[PDB]
Length: 427
Ligand SMILES: OC[C@H]1O[C@@H](O[C@H]2[C@H](O)[C@H](O)[C@H](O[C@H]3[C@H](O)[C@H](O)[C@H](O[C@H]4[C@H](O)[C@H](O)[C@H](O[C@H]5[C@H](O)[C@H](O)[C@H](O)O[C@@H]5CO)O[C@@H]4CO)O[C@@H]3CO)O[C@@H]2CO)[C@@H](O)[C@@H](O)[C@@H]1O
Ligand SMILES: [Zn+2]
Ligand SMILES: [Zn+2]
Ligand SMILES: [Zn+2]
Ligand SMILES: [Zn+2]
Ligand SMILES: [Zn+2]
Ligand SMILES: [Zn+2]
Ligand SMILES: [Zn+2]
Ligand SMILES: [Zn+2]
Ligand SMILES: [Zn+2]
Ligand SMILES: [Zn+2]
Ligand SMILES: [Zn+2]
Ligand SMILES: [Zn+2]
Ligand SMILES: [Zn+2]
Ligand SMILES: [Zn+2]
Ligand SMILES: [Zn+2]
Ligand SMILES: [Zn+2]
Image (cartoon, rainbow, N blue to C red; front, side, top):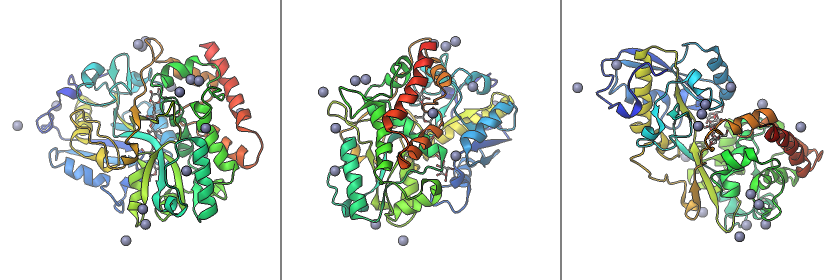
């Protein structure tokens, strides 16, 4: 339900909704930005700048840790207790049950990037706050200490580099952040465009493939197998932290900035947070995930968290919400400040944390075929795997089985393949 009769492309900032006085509530996952100590530009600061062209629109910001679970709970209460949230892991088909359509994708495609990401039946329901790549954060000082001269481009190269970090430095070669279910489920984001160079892989190939997690016999250093085995080998070889069950995310940022951690597998949004986390921001870099496909590396551009607007609020509140979202996207500088690509479609400016991406082919997952937009979500749900769905529990299990030598990676992938295989057949 779009109760405002105006779409995002039609909003002209400064002279749409200038009459409005209301209070909107913004839920998001950036707890760090909801504090005055935040090293960068925090939420209060963005809003103050917003209230300089919409001084009558008050923005209250709520943030929760374990945001993935808290936003999903609120969403299912299906009330008007929130105006904007970052969209949690809901099937693309339910969007209309909870969110205002910003406009039709073909029209949104003229004013924002990734317009078809949070889209269903031709309407865009979410706008990425930032465009991010799936890569690895790395401490250049730790890499230098170990004598690493070329960034690793293959899983074998990466393991050999981790070994050198373990042997020659005091750093954790790869810090798992096991305790954060979202940091573990982050590994699902690398198995498609990065592992295959195939934009159709995530939404077409993967849900029509019965055993997608098996080793690729032709290109064994590629495809989902190679990604999950990277994490498995790093742990089983003893190149991750002493005790995965004691990892702490906030202090991991400080440790990494101080050179106590060499690498963390996290999207490009993590680069600024690592930089700001101590002195030595210039020790923090970002590298493509170490998979090469036919002699070229690939990195998918996808949205960070996408702004969704509560279908249940009044017309004035939807208007104010959409204005704020458009301001965040077009005026705030949030994307640039948080290390990412602006979603505004009159701007590209590949942020600075990307020189090591000079020869990487950046890609965006293609949409499913017509009538198959649901297919990946159906297989996912039937398989109980939760690929790219915050089911970080299956990733934690990789860590636990590698560390306790309970199963091989091929046994793990085999189990997953059998759950997946039945789900694909069933759809
Ligand atoms: O399902 C397949 C589907 O994949 C698509 O993929 C998207 C997916 O739908 C989501 O949009 C997802 O969004 C992830 C973001 O890209 C990003 O990685 C995000 O990272 C969060 C992180 O989860 C966590 O909340 C973290 O919180 C921190 C915070 O940053 C700060 O440090 C604070 O101090 O601590 C808190 C922790 O308490 O913040 C990160 C930054 O926002 O995680 C999102 C997932 O939860 O991205 C997927 C991959 O693109 C489409 O491609 C589609 O085609 C396909 O069908
Ligand atoms: Zn005027
Ligand atoms: Zn109005
Ligand atoms: Zn659902
Ligand atoms: Zn449809
Ligand atoms: Zn339909
Ligand atoms: Zn140097
Ligand atoms: Zn090397
Ligand atoms: Zn947990
Ligand atoms: Zn193959
Ligand atoms: Zn190889
Ligand atoms: Zn293949
Ligand atoms: Zn200092
Ligand atoms: Zn330094
Ligand atoms: Zn080849
Ligand atoms: Zn369709
Ligand atoms: Zn199992």
